[PDB]
Amino acid sequence: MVLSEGEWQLVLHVWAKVEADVAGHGQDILIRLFKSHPETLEKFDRFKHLKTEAEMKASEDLKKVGVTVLTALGAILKKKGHHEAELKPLAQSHATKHKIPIKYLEFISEAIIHVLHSRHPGNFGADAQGAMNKALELFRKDIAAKYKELGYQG
Ligand code: HEM
């Protein structure tokens, strides 16, 4: 697929607001994912044991990981579709080391869109959400094709 420049703009405009607080957004998103789809917490051997949301809010590890997840996503979105080189190492460790099915990437995409919608309603109207969804679908489709080359497709 291919986003228009206008769609990239809407995506990079709401992302410039996320970047004013990357650790807080990272926490919100991962907690939104784990509440919604608790099976995904099992993949994180680091803090599979956190039982409640208050425990999650207080885990410094969970917050570091969130910052690492968002910072890498943001670097991919800034490429505007030209992301081949940033995807490779990423598709390799998620497919061979962590074994993250494509479906979990769909779950975290839904968590990102939920948080942006709550935190940034003025910059995240319908067109901006549609553009973000497009940018994340593009990201999943390219990562899925890379999984397949790497022998995982999952
Ligand atoms: C927006 C999508 C995602 C991005 C850009 C992302 C990126 C990253 C990055 C950059 C790291 C650190 C280096 C590496 O291990 O590759 C990481 C580690 C990790 N990611 Fe992903 N990730 C994404 C989705 C997920 C999801 C959905 C899961 C699980 C349901 C997941 C599971 C993990 C795990 C288990 C680690 C290890 C964390 C730690 O213990 O160090 N990731 N991810």
Image (cartoon, rainbow, N blue to C red):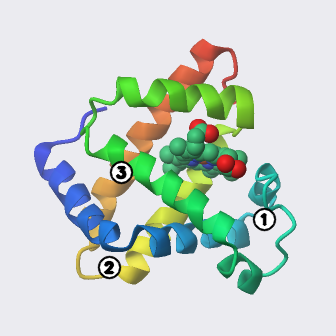
- Front residue of this view, candidates 153 and 47: 47
- Label count reads 3
Residue sitting farthest toward the bottom? 54
Question: Which residue is drawn at the image coordinates 58% and 13% (left, top)?
Answer: 149
Q: Toward which corner of the image does residue 121 lie, by quadrant?
A: bottom left
- The residues bearing labels 3 and 2 have C-alpha atoms spaced at a distance of 17 Å
Q: What residue type is labelled 3?
A: Gly
- Front residue of this view, candidates 12 and 134: 12
Q: Which of marks 1 and 2 is nearer the N terminus?
A: 1
Q: Regarding mark 1 in the picture, which secondary structure is present there?
A: helix
- Front residue of this view, candidates 15 and 105: 15
Q: Toward which corner of the image does residue 113 lie, by quadrant?
A: bottom left
- The residues bearing labels 1 and 3 have C-alpha atoms spaced at a distance of 25 Å
Query: What residue would you read off at disc 1?
Result: 38
Q: Give the position of the N terminus as an image quadrant.
A: top left
Q: Toward which corner of the image does residue 37 lie, by quadrant?
A: bottom right
Q: Give the position of the C terminus as an image quadrant.
A: top right
Query: What residue would you read off at disc 2?
Result: 120
- The residues bearing labels 1 and 2 have C-alpha atoms spaced at a distance of 25 Å
Residue 88 in view, yes or no: yes
Left or right relative to 128: residue 41:
right
Q: Nearer the viewer's eye, disc 1 or disc 3?
A: 3
Query: What residue would you read off at disc 3?
Result: 74
Residue 99 in view, yes or no: no
Residue 60: x, y in percent? 65, 71
Q: What residue type is labelled 1?
A: Pro
Q: Regarding mark 3 in the picture, which secondary structure is present there?
A: helix
Q: What residue type is labelled 2?
A: His
Residue 38: x, y in percent? 78, 65
